[PDB]
Amino acid sequence: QLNALLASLEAENKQLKAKVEELLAKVGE
Amino acid sequence: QLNALLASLEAENKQLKAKVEELLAKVGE
């Protein structure tokens, strides 16, 4: 189950980084 | 080293969630 936790955290991190990119771009409007 | 990777990912996730909160609030301006 440790690899599943790693996988979930990795997925969340990727999603959050993309959300930051989206919101950054929105702030630039 | 697996716990260190978990720890780093957890720290990053917490930081990113807070950055999302900040940028959300900025979008609301």
Image (cartoon, coloured by chain):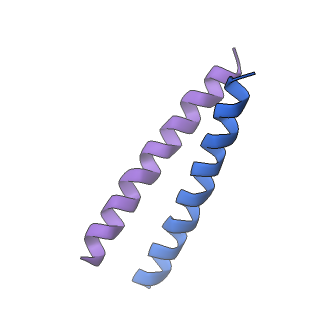
Chain colours: A blue, B purple
**Quadrant holding the N terminus of chain A:** bottom left
Task: Tell me if A26 is positioned left or right of B9 in this view.
Answer: right
- Total label count? 0
Please state which of residues B22 and A26 is positioned toward the viewer in this rendering.
A26
**Quadrant holding the C terminus of chain A:** top right
Residue B28, quarter of the rendered image: top right
Q: Up-down: is A2 above or below B28?
A: below
Q: Up-down: is A19 above or below B5?
A: above
Residue at 43%, 48% (x, y): give it: B14
Task: Tell me if B22 is positioned left or right of A22 in this view.
Answer: left
Q: Tell me where residue A21 appears, x and y as whole percent.
A: 64, 42
Q: Tell me where residue B3 appears, x and y as whole percent.
A: 27, 72
Please state which of residues A28 and A23 is positioned toward the viewer in this rendering.
A28
Residue at 55%, 28% (x, y): give it: B22
Q: Residue furthest top?
A: B29
Residue at 24%, 76% (x, y): give it: B1
Q: Up-down: is B22 above or below B10?
A: above
Task: Tell me if B1 is positioned left or right of B14 in this view.
Answer: left
Residue at 33%, 60% (x, y): give it: B8
Q: Tell me where residue B17 appears, x and y as whole percent.
A: 52, 44
Q: Up-down: is A18 above or below A9?
A: above
